[PDB]
Length: 121
Length: 121
Image (cartoon, rainbow over all chains, first blue to last red; front, top):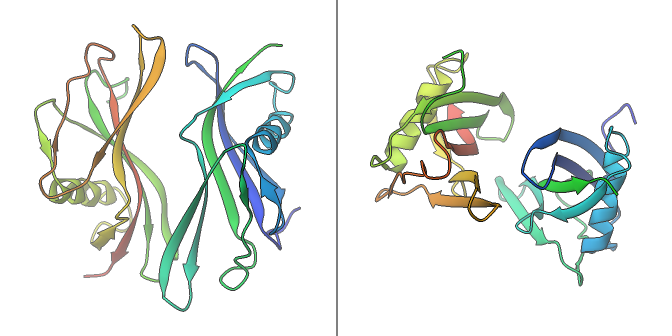
């Protein structure tokens, strides 16, 4: 889309590095629409980062591992409290259900800013 | 300096916003040399962010508050473990003493990536 997204979305900002820590790919920005009620698990997230890398020179690379301390975070301004609120969700096999924040913001961006180790298959 | 810094440094990456959350200033990158043994406290850190804003249009603005969840973080590759290690330090009045990581890296960058609320004096 050319315009601001109309609903919740997953914003993937990933830095790709090799197994020795050398940066291969700079923070690459990609948006994916998501809907409240969806369960986001570790495998689904890895699939979104592979999808993200498809727009790069590293489209055929295997994603070895995501930084284990990586979390999905959403920040918004609560209008009724006049305060900024930030929620964080862990990336696990059980996963978490995407909440509906429409009461505060119609197009919340769920952020995944992390480093990923990649390698040739 | 035009070249890569030769010793430890504090890297300030701040986003300035007003009291309603409007972004006034985009992540602004500034480096300050620091030495192991120095105690970095909340007030010293606020002083570094004011110093950082002096390079911007918001040089006369008062820094109202730093995001309370902001931490100072340093990431490096431990050569003997062949693993990346990340250390985080809280921003408090007691503060923390800057460690000497020269065994692993000669010019570690202590990162402060946070949002700060600013206003006219």
